[PDB]
Amino acid sequence: MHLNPAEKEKLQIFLASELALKRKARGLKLNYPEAVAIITSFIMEGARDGKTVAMLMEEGKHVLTRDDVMEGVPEMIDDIQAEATFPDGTKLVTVHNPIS
Amino acid sequence: MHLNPAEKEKLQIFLASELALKRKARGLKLNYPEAVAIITSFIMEGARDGKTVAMLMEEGKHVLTRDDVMEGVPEMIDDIQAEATFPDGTKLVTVHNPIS
Amino acid sequence: MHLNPAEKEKLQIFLASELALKRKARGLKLNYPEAVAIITSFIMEGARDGKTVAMLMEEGKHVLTRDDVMEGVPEMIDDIQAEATFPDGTKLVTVHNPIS
Amino acid sequence: MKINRQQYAESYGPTVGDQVRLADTDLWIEVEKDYTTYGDEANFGGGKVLREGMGENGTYTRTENVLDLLLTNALILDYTGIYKADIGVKDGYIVGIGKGGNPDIMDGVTPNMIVGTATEVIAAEGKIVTAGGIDTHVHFINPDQVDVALANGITTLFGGGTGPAEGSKATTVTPGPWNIEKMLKSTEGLPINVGILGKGHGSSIAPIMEQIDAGAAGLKIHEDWGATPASIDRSLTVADEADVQVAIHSDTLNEAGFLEDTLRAINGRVIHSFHVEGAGGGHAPDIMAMAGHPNVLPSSTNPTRPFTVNTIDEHLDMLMVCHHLKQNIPEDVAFADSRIRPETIAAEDILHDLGIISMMSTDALAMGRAGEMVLRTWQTADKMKKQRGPLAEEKNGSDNFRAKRYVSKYTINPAIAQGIAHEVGSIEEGKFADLVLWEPKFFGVKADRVIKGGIIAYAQIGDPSASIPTPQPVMGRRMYGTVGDLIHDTNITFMSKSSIQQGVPAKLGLKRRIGTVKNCRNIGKKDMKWNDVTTDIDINPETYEVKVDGEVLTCEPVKELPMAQRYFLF
Amino acid sequence: MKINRQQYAESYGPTVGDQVRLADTDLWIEVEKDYTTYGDEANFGGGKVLREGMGENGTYTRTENVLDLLLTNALILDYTGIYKADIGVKDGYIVGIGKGGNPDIMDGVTPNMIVGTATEVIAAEGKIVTAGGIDTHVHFINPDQVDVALANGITTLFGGGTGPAEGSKATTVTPGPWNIEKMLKSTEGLPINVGILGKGHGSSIAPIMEQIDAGAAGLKIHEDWGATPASIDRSLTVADEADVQVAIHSDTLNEAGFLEDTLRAINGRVIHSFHVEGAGGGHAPDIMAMAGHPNVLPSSTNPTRPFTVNTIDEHLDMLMVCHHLKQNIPEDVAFADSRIRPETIAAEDILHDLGIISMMSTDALAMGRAGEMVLRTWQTADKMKKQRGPLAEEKNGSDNFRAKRYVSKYTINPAIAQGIAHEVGSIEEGKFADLVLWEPKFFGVKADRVIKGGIIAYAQIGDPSASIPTPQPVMGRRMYGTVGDLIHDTNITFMSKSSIQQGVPAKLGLKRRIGTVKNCRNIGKKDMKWNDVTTDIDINPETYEVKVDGEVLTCEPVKELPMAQRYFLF
Amino acid sequence: NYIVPGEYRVAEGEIEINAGREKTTIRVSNTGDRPIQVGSHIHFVEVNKELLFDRAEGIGRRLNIPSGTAARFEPGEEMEVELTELGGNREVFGISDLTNGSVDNKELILQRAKELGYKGVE
Ligand code: NI
Ligand code: NI
Ligand code: NI
Ligand code: NI
């Protein structure tokens, strides 16, 4: 596979997102790391799909809403940042205030 | 996400459980680590759901039966122990003789 | 569970395969590490199922075809090798030119 | 020009009279004073104040009042106060608390807090900064326990063990000169401060004392090795000669005596009573009465902290595993059951709130959680505010009195008890620069950065392959202070005076900083900061009801805690 | 009072005449004798026997017959016996096997096995304890291979390599003085015992000998460097002068000679024949005939162990990768194919069972599996019991004779072959305390705790953040013996007498314990414990049929093994 | 045929503990208000002061129970127990500091016990 250090680490974001998605699907309000994981994995998969950085900066604000998460979680997350390989190489996506 | 050492480690219990559940679903009798993984992940997800320690100590005996596992596996597992964050903080669940 | 070093490492092949399978299912042509991960996990699960080494050496050539992967990926993969616990212990499966 | 309060706090952190919520608790801390000069706040970055000729002095060499490190705009939470200041570090020690910058052009600069060519900067604006936690009940069972401790803000581990041997899995003991030497060498690779306890057991002095001379920093008396009147007596005789502390886990079984017999053997000498409530061990049912005595330094271990609806149910199996007991021996089960009492656990919450139990500790991996001492301290304080109300001592709607009482339990008090408070345990000038930065939203839950001897040792930080350090995954990671030979200069091995005088560090090739244990035998409950209360504690032998000043101490278990499911992935 | 057998065994482990199943095999071991005094068994924990004034002596200092460590109630499986005893360790060495405790009050205490203030305790009741495995065919290719080895109970790695260089990926060789020096320094960070083999190739003595003087512990002759009559001769001349062992992988190609020519070059001198069956290398098809000779110490490597239905199919591609061969060169493929023979693999199972092949080894990462030497030894024994029946030498329905024959293959015999059995390779008084604890259900599969020089180095242990060490995930982890400078005292670097005399350890700054290789040249097949058989082995050059005493040796491959899918996640 | 991995097949018969040693049965009462539990290997005369029994009969003896087990006395509880003889050198040091030498020194042990208030010295 030739996995480098980042590829190994970022597998565990995907895994945490899968965990969190299962918790959401069975009716739980999500906590802080769960919410961060879902939005982060969304961004990295979006890059893999070939979306632009600008698309993801905006889409990232519409993945989870305040009714999906516990009290105070929206205010705990000032931004989420993630890097992934876009068609034009590694880029950084910053999503400000992803959950209103 | 702010993952601490235990949060990182415990991701791999969830993963091993997902692996084992797929093996069970395609008709395989489960082996020792597969059985332990399923019951352990069940407990940690139960805590996340807000069950009590006492509920899980008993539910853990009804997750897998002897027909779900290989010969000798029930007798190999004297107990399963797992810690997770309940609504009232980290607690330990001990399930004695989980597979009769 | 008593996980040894290889059992821990090989969890991340299963995980990478699950990631890659999701990417394929949403219509993406797979890249080099994705393709390797899918075929590798296929082999290890085949061993768990009780297939022979000889069966998997041949089945491994029919998991992904060139239309499933990006340009040049078939030619990048000269072989895939994986070890797993068969009913008769650990064995090595070598699949030559898995994608024509 | 004037700046409104909200905007000021957002830019520089809070100032005098502002309050901050601790994590998702109901606890609020208030800034008591601020060492700054408004308009001359230090800050670092593009176009900011700490630049040459401006807030950074360009004239002075390092030895001329210049710092190695300035933490700008810290909100300090310490037994000494809750207040706003810059913190200056040099040679690995805190040398100034006050106002940093450049006396050329700024008013009110603390004279030895010059930002110069030699000065690194850590921005603490908007952070709470505390001393590193001092955990004095550590079982050395699994080296993976060190990162667990660092991640919740612990910087010193005192205790014993050789790894997952049954002796160590039960008791905080590294037995005898050879095991002690081996563990001192192991310690060279552990990125945290360490002190090692020998076995406080014997009926002759020499077998016990030779452990102190070998490099132990104290002793543990534990019932699993025989907490007999003789072992108690000989250990305290050794400790009084050597100037080290003795920890005790007393005779739960009451085999050779009741509590009063243990107190008679102690004979008024200083002792640290571990897990004083007794689930973790001790004379059943009344061992918590220890905490009323003037010569006892009492700590709790963490699984009973605080009293919750799941607390009792987890304990039996936990205890059986720790102490190598058998389910098929009725007397083993009876012994275990005798230790587990909701009456004393409930009273333990209240005794903490009253300043009668002075310390917290983990009991890491032997009926305790290595990364939850700090966590459970604040959960206890929060529960007590909810159930008992603000303490009478409070004012301005703040919880500052409670906050000082509780922070002392895991910082200064354990340091005083083990004779190491000259080096660690509080944010004071002259002490080692073991500092923990917390975002208020994560306070007591997950440390931001843990500074050890003036260099960051552990941090919550993101993708090492990214353009900046903030992108995911943000996780706890060892930093440069732990790498190469820097691990030697950023950590202290605490040792007895006799082992130091006898040259044990050179004999073993120890390269870590060597700390001297001292002033352990001349202290008492009166010396426990904000937790100095002595009183007659009565425990009913039949009902386990706990009374202080003729009043039953009881409270309800809670179904939910803060600092819990909002934060943790599992 | 009397205790029934079932309850006694549950409390203290088995005693005389009791049997234990090895993992999920059909193999049963029987306790032959027991050193205890019934009623005075040592045990540790809450309210247990090893307490001051009771089973722990409170009088004696460490130097006065007191132990650093007592393993209580061990079921020892060793070439010397299968029996029940306490094991006492001091200064990193096994000093007593017998009965530990306190002579004050207990009968039958071995005089130097006093439990005192200085004594740590490991509970071995219900465990099988063996010597650490001695793997003498290790390629140093990937440092991650060390934990793999520890997890299956291996404590010594003998072999060669510099990492994933093609020379090392093919051959157990660290070539020349500089590479040897570099790998001796690397070894300072490897938590396992190590000895390094130089290149056994040359036609002049000096290039070969200077490797021994540089710190090599032996030599490897390998066909990939030219296993010529000259290289064989010069290497053995060097070995006879230096008192080190030579391992040989002979000329498969028969390029410069047939087997008889290699034997003539050896000229009756002592040699260790690697992978004697020949899939791993050697004169095709008849190299296994080596194992009949009195001057040959024969080992197998592990992928042919035992003969299974998938064995042949994995080998061609494995061999091509190891030896840097090309699929498009017909003679490369012919060479590979010549090595892979079901006839000799089947006979190899039987030769092990008969005590004609004396040793097992891995061939780690170069046609072998670093963590399966112990595993496959027991799978072979189990297969042979199933196909050949209990050996004639057995009695009482036990498999003790087979068990001693097979445990010797990976413990004492490799140690004797490499001249290191004065230090390691068996549970005997005076030897280094490299000990492996196994739960019987996991015997030979996953080690519980691996003790190195008297300190736990590796363990299957759970959540470091938990209240106790048993909660999930339970996985193999490095323990305190591997941390800091303790790695130096818990491991041995084995070196030639000449390098030690010439001060190589001081020159290179080696801090590990230094072991001397000796008594390698005066031994033979007769010195291989329980595996000392010499005989004429005939291998048919056309059919590959193997005959001993006029009898064809053959058996069937099996479709399933124990110690396999019940245990492993992948 | 069913395989339990690592299972025992124990031999027939029973294990006699403390074989060949004199046994003595005595009555013992917990006169205190908290439970007292006594291990197999504590010198019996040196147990908790508030256990009432003929202290002389505990000298040089311990409970005749399996190694690592105990006798538990609830408050006010009287029980009959069986003692066995100490072995080895028959010396005891430490514990309650009643002996510190040979257990043969019955008069000294009892003098110390009486002075310190160990119940049941005649
Ligand atoms: Ni304790
Ligand atoms: Ni403890
Ligand atoms: Ni070879
Ligand atoms: Ni090899």
Image (cartoon, coloured by chain):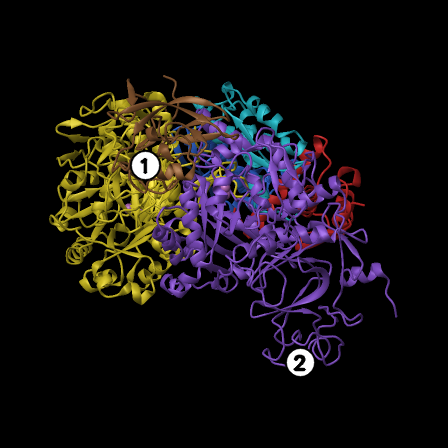
Chain colours: A red, B cyan, C blue, D purple, E yellow, F brown
- Residue E358 rendering spot, x and y as whole percentages: 21, 38
For the residue pair D265 and E482, the one nearer the viewer reads as: D265
Query: Residue A25, located in which quarter of the rendered image?
Result: top right
Q: Seen from this angle, which residue lies furthest front?
A: F122
Can the viewer see residue E303?
no
Residue identifier under label 2: D58
- At a point 26% along the width and 50% down the height, the residue shown is E223
Three-letter amino acid code at disc 1? Val
Q: In the picture provided, is E498 more to the left or to the right than D567?
A: left
Give neighbour class at mark 2: few <14, some 14-19, many 20+ (Cα, 10 Å).
some
Quarter of the image for the N terminus of chain E: give it: top left
Q: Seen from this angle, which residue lies furthest bottom?
A: D59
State which chain disc 2 sits on. D
- Residue E458 rendering spot, x and y as whole percentages: 41, 44
For the residue pair A59 and D505, the one nearer the viewer reads as: D505
For the residue pair E172 and D77, the one nearer the viewer reads as: D77
Can the viewer see residue C41?
yes
- Residue E445 rendering spot, x and y as whole percentages: 38, 34
Three-letter amino acid code at disc 2? Gly
Give neighbour class at mark 1: few <14, some 14-19, many 20+ (Cα, 10 Å).
many
Q: Mark 1 near mark 2, Cβ–Cβ under 8 Å?
A: no
Is residue D11 placed above or below F1 in the rendered structure? below
Residue identifier under label 1: E129
Q: In the picture provided, is E71 more to the left or to the right than D69?
A: left
